[PDB]
Image (tube, rainbow, N blue to C red):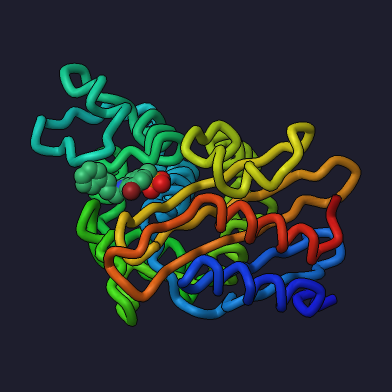
Length: 269
Ligand SMILES: O=c1cc(CP(=O)(O)O)c2ccc(Br)cc2n1/C=C\Cc1ccccc1
């Protein structure tokens, strides 16, 4: 049940047309069948760390009474670019749960930096990932510096396989308690930034939760998702891209096309 050869040639053609590298790992949680293409290479996380950030906050809420309801107040100076929720509550503040929702569902950069600070920074999120058995994931920096996406730089990277493996543990496995797991799933389900990526490859009658990342350089963008096809076990997948030149543009269509190939590889309709 290594079904990559069904789609290995098509993946090569897609990345050749893209002009960069495409990394995919897709897992059929029923059979354990998998599709791998560059699944062990490091790709820049960009915003995609925010989903894991939200899961780490949910993990801490299992042990720390009232953490989700804590009001957080922040100054104008916290409002880095692409903070579309936290800019509307500057004068009021937001709860930890609302920052978590905004980080997942709007990719809110201020909200992400505020939650990172609650966990003790990039090392604290890295420590949470180590605790669920993820030895690949590393966050090194804050928003926006983590977006540099420098070729060969392992800072602020993971692998498609490690991302998929961790996403499965947190959404479908036992890394979170049942209520926290369902909150994590509900946050990803309600994401607004991913309609042109993995969701574009999935029929309307299937449930999907995703988290996007877009670095804005080096044709670097991504998406991961848990897909619930009707009448079959859920699919977990990660689609990451990078390109050699700083000027190179990311492509949402390439991410959708890659997700389509992964689902075709797993034999899902
Ligand atoms: O930090 C982010 C977050 C998003 C949303 P996503 O990651 O979940 O897809 C984003 C989307 C498209 C692009 Br192009 C860059 C993005 N960036 C990085 C830069 C954002 C920015 C905006 C203005 C000026 C400088 C940087």
